[PDB]
Length: 295
Length: 296
Ligand SMILES: N[C@@H](CCCC[NH3+])C(=O)O
Ligand SMILES: N[C@@H](CCCC[NH3+])C(=O)O
Image 1 (spheres, rainbow over the protein chains, first blue to last red):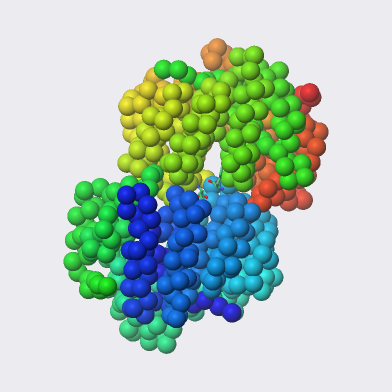
Image 2 (image 1 turned 120 degrees about the vertical axis):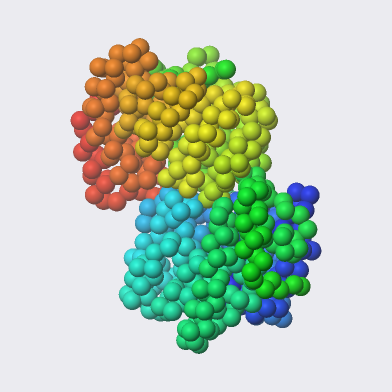
């Protein structure tokens, strides 16, 4: 009982300080129409930290209602540095039609490996839908060790894999060599193919917000072991994959979506803000080299 | 500039049956007041601010301002958040409820840019009229408030008067005070309290002061009196306990020490925080033996 394939960490477009819910549904439809397998509402790319609870819940509802009749699954962003908050988000996502949940490792409080095990066990025991771990130590300040990830996969029936955003291909080999039954998901666009070629079964992408057809083609070429095609797209996408992180995600990707005319206003919620005027031109310069799909 | 300096304690938040033990909390603050502590920091990183509800976060601030009232011990209320609107709400509550100042941690997880950090703290400083002390701890937040950003906020905002550094970078400490000697650098790292104070730091926000407030206060006050021989001596004596209090993630070791010292009733954390390992439980207990722990 898995959620795999090409997935998009959806941005959360704002307009006049409010979630633009019409653009939000429209962007998800654009993902559905270009071969995306799942959408991740209210992730790191979705500015989950500055959204209220009612906005976090609304973006989940818009994702589930848009994907009805489609196979874009909804891996609802339900992570938190407080276990009771993460259990509450997991319980909401289940009761409102989400196919699974993405649960980021607790940030700022830096739990121990024992605490991470108990944190995700409480989340996994509160629902009966798949739970995908999310490891990003550069943002959280903590690391879910390989041993902890493997234990959670084997002890909790709904925990089926991990979204790795650590730039450590050695750990990816370590995970699948010792536990080949888990679903390793790439959370780093620049190394999507190396993660997929070693046995990864999907991506949760930032670049797919701008180029969903290319991320989708890459992931599915890799899943069919057509590595000559999968690597080609991964190499061609490297420049945009790196320039989308010249500043902290999701500042560059939202700037690109605005430059592509896909969102109406380049609005962030503080402490996030607009990029520099130099980076504004660099992102626009890199975008001119790629085929950006419309609506 | 209105300042809050000296020896300060990042108060732990004791729980009992899943609720904040408020009688124990006010008793811990009195013990801090009675051992020469100049200010208390409610609901910091040590106070498990991430797992406290909004009502519990507000309650601990209220208890701190009430326990310290009638004394010169100030309340530097923890009011940080990775959401600017959340941090502004916390700053406004602390103001309207008697806090002398606020401690505002750098936004975690979302990693704001240097421009975003400036606008974040500018909005906080303009929302309140009490002193604002920045809090830099890159190992926990994933971002760093650069020296240039800290100095800009200090010079552009009336209420921004310094920073709590928890970065293990004494080079940065020299950088701050060499270019802006009027700021109040506060040590957020117990093991290097004296080196920060000897270069011009004006106080500490301590984890070890929960267990040994008399020693942290004496250390800070020796340094402020330029008695660097006695300040370093205590800093050296405290090195073993200062490091064992971080053998696991704060506040797991300090709460274990407070429990082992009989200062709190139950060794209760709120998930994802939990009790330390068996070996670390013994290591903390062994290091505690070499120190005189004050009672109530
Ligand atoms: N500052 C809080 C807000 C959570 C709102 C719901 N995602 C956090 O990032 O954990
Ligand atoms: N867990 C969230 C919400 C905290 C709310 C105030 N205690 C955070 O760390 O920001």
